[PDB]
Amino acid sequence: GTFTSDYSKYLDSRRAQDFXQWLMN
Image 1 (spheres, rainbow, N blue to C red):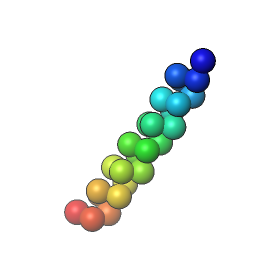
Image 2 (cartoon, one colour):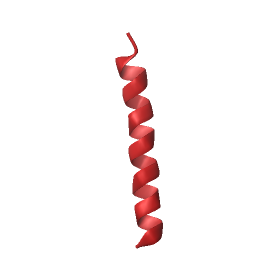
Image 3 (cartoon, rainbow, N blue to C red):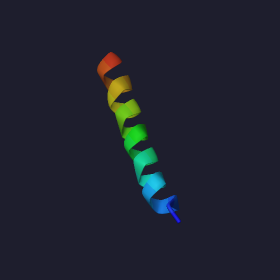
Image 4 (cartoon, one colour):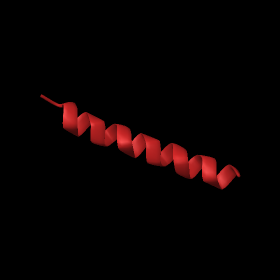
């Protein structure tokens, strides 16, 4: 299956959001 690979992409998405949020604040 692709669960772990897809979860890694989700972790990238969280990091992108955390970076976004930090830049704004």
